[PDB]
Image 1 (cartoon, rainbow, N blue to C red):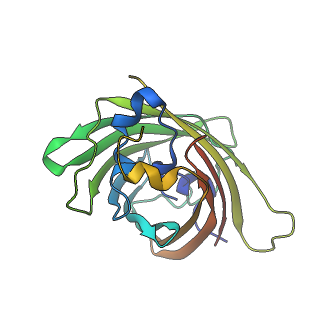
Image 2: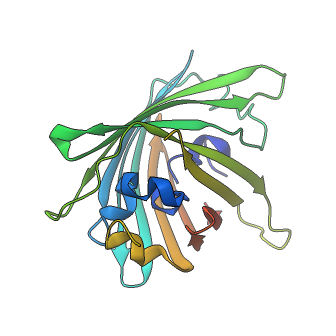
Length: 225
């Protein structure tokens, strides 16, 4: 059993699978960084509770898009919504606001996730994000825009392990290929996710597998603890 609720890990567990409409293709940093990939770092501040600090490497390994993350959680409350497992098993729609970070040749993002709590309250998870390309090749630095998300969470009835089935759609909004990296996403791409976590000393790991179809902004993944 994970020591934190599955919904709190959704944003940490591949924005290169977002659908960028044709008029916005010049603003897709995530795909432009491929195949060498990017480092994605966040601080996630759970209001009135602790924080996650995450560092991920997102890159291709052969045909597979891999997201490997180290997560460190500190300052959580014993009977808070996170360590107390008081969050509903669902996920709200969010708008991820992206800005260019010209000095880091990358991007920043900010957004606040709303986690529904079982008593009808809301737990906020304030996200600060920075992404830096790994390669030396040119990348696309975007104008200000956002990603609009939709996520559904479910279970595999045949799976005895603690797990999460996730389906997600993401479209960019708020504004031939525009990068060579974009062309690595034209069809269905297998995904592997590996997370190593420690939250207030509770150690855990998650492995996810599935596929992404960036033409429709879709992710299909199953994660196991």
